Image (cartoon, coloured by chain):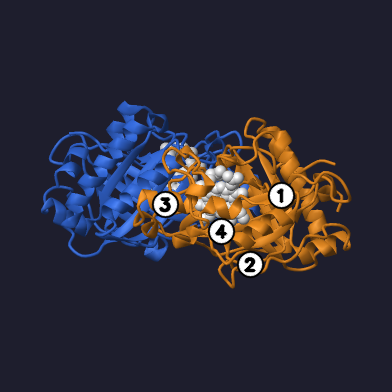
Chain colours: A blue, B orange
Amino acid sequence: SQVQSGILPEHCRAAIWIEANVKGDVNALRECSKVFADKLAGFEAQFPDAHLGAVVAFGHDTWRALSGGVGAEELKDFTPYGKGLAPATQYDVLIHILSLRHDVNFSVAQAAMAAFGDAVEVKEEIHGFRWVEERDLSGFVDGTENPAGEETRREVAVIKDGVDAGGSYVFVQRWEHNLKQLNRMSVHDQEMMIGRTKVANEEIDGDERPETSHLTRVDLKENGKGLKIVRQSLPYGTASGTHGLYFCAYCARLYNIEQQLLSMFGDTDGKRDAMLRFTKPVTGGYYFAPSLDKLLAL
Amino acid sequence: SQVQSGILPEHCRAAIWIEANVKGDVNALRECSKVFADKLAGFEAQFPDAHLGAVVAFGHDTWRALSGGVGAEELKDFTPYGKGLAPATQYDVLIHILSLRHDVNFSVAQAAMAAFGDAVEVKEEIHGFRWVEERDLSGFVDGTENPAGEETRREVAVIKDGVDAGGSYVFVQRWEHNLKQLNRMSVHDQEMMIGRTKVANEEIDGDERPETSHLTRVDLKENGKGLKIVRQSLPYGTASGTHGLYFCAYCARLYNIEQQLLSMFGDTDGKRDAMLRFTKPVTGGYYFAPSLDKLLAL
Ligand code: HEM
Ligand code: HEM
């Protein structure tokens, strides 16, 4: 059972995320996904230069109908966390395209619109870009402790056996940064908000940083082992308008993601992530990405 | 006199254009431009291999004020052409940033906003990207006959002497492509529309292509010599929403640009550019880019 090509590649330079709702018969998606998968393989062969991959994933209601209610038992509609502090915008279809080349990405995105256009209504399209030194627009490096290498990323993100082998759970959440509020903070204040030093990007030990620090919020364990995720987030936006981080995570279990959300947004222990001092999520949804084999034969 | 670094570089991968109006006192721009140019010089040293360049240019009324009526006598407000076919959105300040790296462009743009933000209200920010094979989103190679090499480009784009030595005239015009309308045309018909063959990008002899063809519209001569411009246009937009070409031209004389506009939009001989079958301009403005010396010396 083959994984879809966009989950495992590391250090993309650019990505496109399309979120869309079914219009009409959900069953049309079966043929759309096969058409797009074929176009995608063609682009991957045409531009090996790009290290291109993509993922098609589906929301609870849509996947339940496409799978006939079999498998993906964890999948559910994203609903608001923190009593609304993390809003919900659950759509039916997620397409995630990533590579080293924005120009190739755009061609693949056009192919996706051609494949799905008559079956969906697009609600969001975000073009992510890797920024200097792989930093978030806040000036902090983003990705350091992400799982590295195919073996470890596969362990964290790709379902290993069962009816869903080769699939993955996906979470996407667009954040809007208020950089003027960030810059009112001393660098020490910022570093206590994140849990790592800003320029040097060294971790502050768990006892030196407040329990509201981001790293304390998301360093969660079960049975003494950390709940890991594979993050494909990138910056997005304009300099003069809206900008921030398009957050994107893959995980073999929805649980690891949900537990970090419950932690960050006050649900678990009443404390909230200190990053909410300067940035806020404005979308959110859960999706199931089937194995490529399952995607090809819906 | 030194030219601003953004005019002459060839084959940028990505650009950012910012159009803005003055908010308070126009004289605040004097310190804003010096601050930004200082910041730009720092990014050009920090990223010596990115081919980074930027241009600050000014609308008619804002330049008259900043320069005490001195020079830039050609500079005027952009006004509609073709009885409204080409609308006018003349603003006060144009900032154009280009390089091989979008991530570096975004840093420069943030610096532009840190420097001009208090003094202006941004009307538009557009991120351009070079597409596959340097093709416009219509599928036609864009740029083939552009002036190449620093000598020829300086002849065309940089003012040679006089009070304005080192400066240039800029025209920006965002177009919205309707690729559905494009793809209803046969390839032959598209080629007759542009004036070059589509895949091979070979010229079609002027006698074998309609006088409404783009090339016939824009390949103009005065006194037996071609009216050249230096184009920096790039594709922009999203696959599912608005997309097209952000047109951008530099010229030593406003006359070369205006003559092509008069031709394309039916004002010269009543014939209109055949590209209007599928795309349309929705903005337009004229700006004056002073040499880098005046920009620091305002
Ligand atoms: C629901 C949203 C998010 C989740 C679930 C999440 C999850 C994580 C995880 C699991 C880590 C690695 C922690 C470790 O084991 O060391 C991490 C690190 C980090 N995150 Fe978040 N993150 C989220 C949102 C954000 C946002 C919005 C930003 C910035 C604006 C951000 C910036 C960072 C930074 C700078 C690091 C440290 C560098 C790294 O290890 O990647 N995160 N995040
Ligand atoms: C939707 C907007 C436009 C598109 C898709 C477009 C596309 C093209 C293409 C495909 C070429 C031939 C390849 C090349 O030599 O670059 C070309 C040439 C050219 N274009 Fe455009 N163009 C657009 C707008 C404009 C405008 C508004 C102007 C001038 C005001 C202009 C001026 C020129 C010039 C001067 C040439 C070179 C002609 C020659 O000497 O062969 N273009 N354009």
> Residue type at mark 4?
Arg
Mark 1 highlights which residue? B251
Mark 1 element type: strand
Q: Is residue A201 above or below residue B265?
A: above
Which image quarter: residue B42?
A: top right
Chain letter for mark 3, please. B
Name the foreground residue: B46 vs A281: B46
Q: Quick check: is the Cβ at mark 1 less than 8 Å away from ligand 2? A: no
The residue where tag 2 is placed is B89
**Reading the chain from its start, which is encountered first: label 3 or label 4?**
4
Left or right position of A77 against A135: left
Indicate the position of residue A239 as horizontal and vertical percent values: 59, 53
Q: Are marks 1 and 2 on the same chain?
A: yes
Q: Residues within 10 Å of mark 4 (few under 14, many from 20)?
A: many
* Front residue (pair A185, A102): A102
| Residue B174 numbered tag | 4
The answer to which quarter of the image holds residue B78 is: bottom right
The residue at the point 53 percent across, 53 percent down is B214
User: Which one is in front in this view, the residue at disc 3 or the one at disc 4?
Assistant: 3
Would you call the spot at circle 3 few (<14 residues within 10 Å), some (14-19), or many (20 or more)? many
**Can residue B21 be seen in the rendering of this structure?**
yes
- Number of marks present in the image shown: 4
Q: CA distance from mark 1 to mark 2?
A: 20 Å
